[PDB]
Image (cartoon, coloured by chain):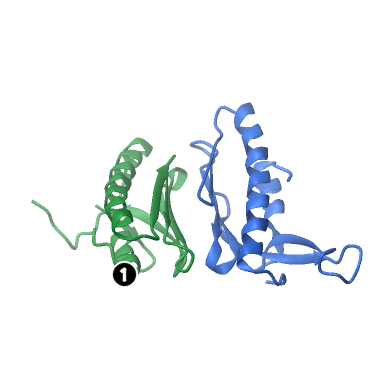
Chain colours: A blue, B green
């Protein structure tokens, strides 16, 4: 999407994001009896229990996307998009986000609304 | 679309995904870029950097198995008894009547 990134750059960005997400969800896992989180090989699994269901969040490297499956709202696909220019016209000052280009929403926003997790 | 309890769903889904896993473990040995994992009701099938990653997961509140394919996108499979067919239930995408086994045959070349 908006960001002009190589596959290697994608992997770094996605790994950084999912590592941060994982540690936030590990906190949630400790506080709640119904929440279990796993992470292996680019795939983050979040079982919210028998009433909520299971979330899957995974790297899709050929598309340079992060894909999502939600039991509340279904499937979505996130591109790495530059939403803020930052300090300069320089691309190294730009703020990038994971955005679902069908509606412009962010992955952070979905997690906040559905799971109460603020990344 | 079958009238089953949540406990029955879990048994049926676990049986199916266990069978699928062992078929994919054979495939893992015979193809260098294929890796399969199965944990907490989620089957991950990484076909490497050109093909991408398949996810196949239980979605218990809907009594479905959900799929995400890098070639053809998301689908939701119900446990369905069709009256075409006899024996001495199948996992079906009810939008077109196809089975999950058929998709895996066509996309990945695994004949289940």
Relative image position of residue B76 (x, y in whole percent): 42, 58
| Picture mark count | 1
Please name the residue shown 33% across and 55% down the image: B28
Residue for badge 1? B106
- Residue A110, placed above or below residue A100: above
Residue plotted at (29% across, 60% down): B101
- x then y, percent, for residue B84: 19, 63
Nearest the camera: A7 or A61?
Answer: A7
Left or right of A94, for residue B56: left
Q: Chain of mark 1?
A: B
Count neighbours of disc 1 (C-alpha within 10 A) and say few if under 14, some if 14 to 19, many if 20 or more.
few
Residue depicted at 67% across the width and 51% down the height: A17
Residue closer to the observer: A7 or A21: A7
**A17 horizontally vs B15: left or right:** right
Is A92 positioned to the left or the right of B65 in the image?
right
Query: How far across and how far down the image is residue B16, in percent?
Result: 29, 48
- Dot 1: what SS? helix
Q: Residue furthest left?
A: B88
Quadrant containing the N terminus of chain B in the rendered view: bottom left
- Name which residue lies at 31% across and 39% down: B11
């Amino acid at each position: 999407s908006m960001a002009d990134i190589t596959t290697a750059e994608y992997h770094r960005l996605a790994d950084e994001y999912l590592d941060a997400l994982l540690s936030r969800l590990e906190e949630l896992q400790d506080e709640r009896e119904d929440v279990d989180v796993e992470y292996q090989s680019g795939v983050l699994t979040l079982n919210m229990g028998p009433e909520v269901g299971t979330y899957v969040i995974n790297k899709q490297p050929p598309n340079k996307q992060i894909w999502l499956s939600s039991p509340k709202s279904g499937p979505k696909r996130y591109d790495y998009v530059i939403t803020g220019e930052g300090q300069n016209e320089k691309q190294d000052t730009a703020v990038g986000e994971w955005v679902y280009l069908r509606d412009g929403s962010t992955l952070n926003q979905l997690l906040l609304e559905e799971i109460g997790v603020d990344l």
